[PDB]
């Protein structure tokens, strides 16, 4: 009843968030997280990339294919690295628009209300995953 | 990098929830909301549903076609205004969700209602709106 309305509002929020994210940063939310994971701790196997981001094999292959096509990752038992373009685009030399977006996003919520949001999100998922039979 | 992860965790949660909800209740989250809305507030025009659900005409047309084909809704013309079309729930829809739910569906409904308290539920939605408002107000 009220629980169903919370889940639906979360679906509408995700769809709005994902569209806004891709328009402002030029990369989808999922593909942006792939690059963040690679830039922090690379190289990684694509099986490990499926685990860390929680997506199936068919999905990861599609994400990584678009990422290599757009010059952000390279693949050589399949290892995956971020390119120099990715490190520059996200970390060492981002555009003024991306710096202004990134800085503005991190100030939307405080650390307390951000931590409480993720705490409730995990409590919700655990409850839903623990439902009868 | 902290905010970008939260948004991604919110996406993964949504995808996981949507799949679980459809399997557990036998109806997708969006189509289930359409029926809940219709069982409370029918008759409703297709346009009203688009605004309430925050989805375009193509999406609602798909949802309503699926619900109509499976016997959960009907679309009938107003006898006084023949070209006006009104959406209604069926007896099957009221039975499936409210008056004759399967033992499993009743157990899922009750279990879902006791996951989060009313306070942490309302605080979550408040933080969600504050997040949406902030993303909408980003430069350009």
Image: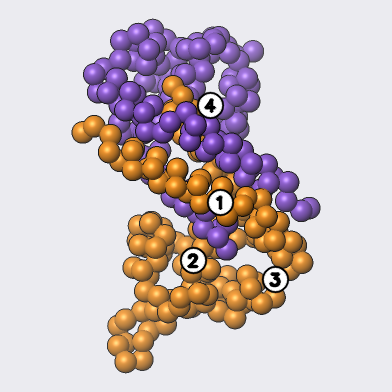
Chain colours: A purple, B orange
Residue A38 vs residue B109, the one in the foreground:
B109
Residue at the location (60% across, 60% down)?
Answer: B27
- What secondary structure is marked by label 3? loop
N-terminal-most mark, 2 or 3: 2
- Which dot, 1 or 2, sits closer to the camera? 1
Can marks 2 and 3 be said to lie on one chain?
Answer: yes
Place residue A47 in its image quadrant. Answer: top right
Label 2 SS: helix
- Asked if labels 1 and 3 share a chain, the reply is yes
Q: Which residue is mark 2?
A: B34
Give the residue at mark 4.
Answer: A61
- Estimate how packed mark 2 is, as few (under 14), some (14 to 19) or many (20 or more) residues with alpha carbons within 10 Å: many
What is the chain identity of the residue bearing mark 2? B
- In the image, is B82 to the left or to the right of A49? left
Report the residue marked by disc 1.
B119
Image depth: mark 4 or mark 2 in front: 2
Circle 3 crowding by C-alpha within 10 Å: few under 14, some 14–19, many from 20: some
The image position of residue B117, as x and y in percent, is 61, 52
Residue B101's label in the rendered image is 3
Q: Is residue B135 above or below residue B109?
A: above
């Amino acid at each position: 009843q009220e629980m169903e309305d919370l889940l639906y509002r979360l679906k509408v929020a995700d769809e709005t968030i994902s569209n806004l994210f891709e328009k402002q940063l030029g990369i989808s939310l999922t593909r942006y997280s792939i690059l963040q994971t690679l830039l922090k701790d690379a190289p990684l196997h694509q099986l490990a990339l499926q685990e860390r981001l929680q997506i199936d094999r068919a999905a990861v292959t599609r994400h990584l294919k678009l990422l290599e096509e757009s010059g952000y990752i390279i693949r050589k038992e399949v290892l995956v690295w971020p390119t120099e373009q990715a490190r520059e685009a996200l970390i060492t030399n981002p555009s003024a628009h991306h710096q202004a977006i990134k800085t503005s996003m991190n100030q939307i919520l405080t650390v307390e209300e951000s931590e409480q949001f993720l705490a409730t999100l995990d409590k919700l998922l655990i409850g839903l995953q623990n439902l009868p039979i």
